[PDB]
Each structure stands twice: as structure tokens, then as C-alpha cells.
Image (cartoon, coloured by chain):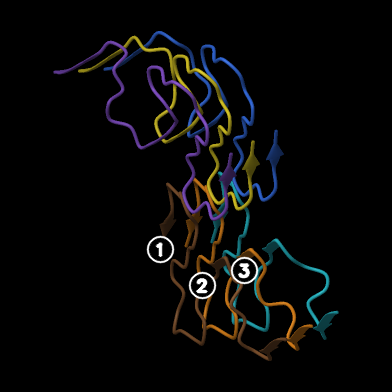
Chain colours: A yellow, B blue, C purple, D cyan, E orange, F brown
């Protein structure tokens, strides 16, 4: 008997690429990328 | 007996590439891309 | 009997790439990427 | 005085995505693509 | 006086994604891709 | 006076993604990718 109780709100379980989550102040250079050679933020 | 209880749905998995989620202040340079060589944000 | 009770608590994840979590002051150079050679933030 | 002497190397740069170069034996599964989820080779 | 003497050409430039170089025996599963979730080779 | 003599000895490589170099026996599972979750080779 396999009883899997998952009352969550997502379907990810491998790679989760996302910035923030709740609430931040100011995003002055928010970047999230693998092998990203080159990026300038004021 | 396979009882899978997932109160959410069936989509978005393996790779989740997306910025934000709830609500941020200001997106001054929000970028999310792998192998992205080149990007300038004021 | 396999009783898995997970009320929105995915602690065991593969790869979780995300900045912040609760709330910060100012994001002046928030970057999260593996093998990222090159990045300038004012 | 800017003297740039480049006998070769004027066509590709930044991102060089290509398989092989001189000569291999057998290509039984030669793949080169970023974010490529799904591929089966016998 | 800037004297740049570069005989050779193609070889590398920021990102060099390529398999092999001289000559191998057998390529039974040659793959080169970042963030590549999924690949089966016999 | 800047005398740069580079006949076959470059330094600006940044990212060099490539398998092998001289010559191997058998490539039964040759993979080169960052953040590659998932790969099976016989």
C-alpha cells in the first residue's frame, strides 16, 4: 500500500531556476543562469 | 495499490526557468538564461 | 504500509537555484549561476 | 598604432558549438546542445 | 605600438563547446551540453 | 612597445568544454556538461 500525501503547490524535483521567493527590496542585478559569461548591471 | 495524492496538478517539472514568484519591488536586471553571453541593464 | 505525510514541505530537493528566501534590504549584485565567468555590478 | 595580425580566426567566437574537428572513429551518440532534455542513441 | 602576432586562428573564444580534438577510438555516448537533463546511450 | 608572439600558445580561453585531447581507447560514456542531472550509458 503506497500512500503518498503531498498537499503542496508545485511539481518540481530536479532543477529549480528562479529568483526571489517571497518579496525583496530592489533587484539591481538579479541574474540566475549557468555558464553565463557576460553581464553588467548598474 | 498506488495512491498518489497531489493537490496541485500535473505540469512544470525537471527544469523550472522563471523569474519572480509572488511579488518583488523593482526588476532592474532580471535575467534567467543558461549560456547567455551578453546582457547590460541600467 | 507506506504513509508519506508531506504537507507542503519539499526539503529533499535535487537542485534549488534561487536567491533570497524571506526578505532582504537591497539586491545590488544578486547572481546565482554555476561556471559564470564574468559579471559586473555597480 | 594598432597592428592586428590574425592569419586566421575570423568567423567564430564567443560561443563555439560544434562536434568533432579533425576526424573520429564512430559517432554513436554525438550530441551538443544546451538545455536538451531528451535523447536516445543506440 | 601594439604588435599582435597571432598566426593560428580558430581554437577558443570565451566558450568552446566541442567534442574530441585529434582522433579517438569510438564515440559511444559523446555528449557536451550544459543543463542537459536526459540522455541514454547504448 | 607591446610585442605579443603567439604562434600556438593562446591564453584567453575562458571556458574550454571538450572531451579527450590526444587519443583514447573507447568512449563508453563520454559526457561534459555542467548541471547535467541525468545520463545513462551502457
The percent coordinates of residue A23 (x first, y second) are 47, 14
Element marked by disc 1: loop
Question: Which picture quadrant has residue A39?
Answer: top right
Sequence-wise first label, 2 or 1: 2
Using the image, name the chain to which the residue with label 1 belongs. F
Looking at the rendered structure, the number of numbered marks drawn on it comes to 3
Element marked by disc 2: loop
Mark 3: give few (<14), some (14-19) or many (20+) Cα within 10 Å: many
The percent coordinates of residue C13 (x first, y second) are 33, 32
The percent coordinates of residue F1 (x first, y second) are 72, 86
Say above or below: C39 vs D11. Answer: above
For the residues marked 1 and 3, what is the alpha-carbon distance in whole angstroms?
22 Å
Same chain under badges 1 and 3? The reply is no
The percent coordinates of residue D38 (x first, y second) are 56, 45
Question: Which picture quadrant has residue C23?
Answer: top left
Using the image, name the chain to which the residue with label 2 belongs. F
- The numbered disc on residue E18 is 3
Q: Which residue is mark 2?
A: F19
The structure residue drawn at horizontal position 43% and vertical position 53%, both measured from the top left corner, is F39
Q: Which residue is mark 1?
A: F42
Location of the C terminus of chain A (image quadrant) = top right
For the residues marked 2 and 1, what is the alpha-carbon distance in whole angstroms?
18 Å
Question: Which picture quadrant has residue B19?
Answer: top right
**Viewed as shown, does residue B26 lie left or right of F29?**
right
Camera-nearest residue between B18 and B9: B18
Element marked by disc 3: loop
Same chain under badges 2 and 3? The reply is no
| Mark whose residue sits in front, 1 or 3 | 3
Say above or below: E33 vs D4. Answer: above
Mark 2: give few (<14), some (14-19) or many (20+) Cα within 10 Å: some
Say above or below: E24 vs B14. Answer: below
Camera-nearest residue between D1 and C35: D1
Amino acid at each position: 500500500d503506497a500512500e503518498f500525501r503531498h498537499d503542496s503547490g508545485y511539481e518540481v524535483h530536479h532543477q529549480k531556476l528562479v529568483f526571489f521567493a517571497e518579496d525583496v527590496g530592489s533587484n539591481k542585478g538579479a541574474i540566475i543562469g549557468l555558464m553565463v559569461g557576460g553581464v553588467v548591471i548598474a
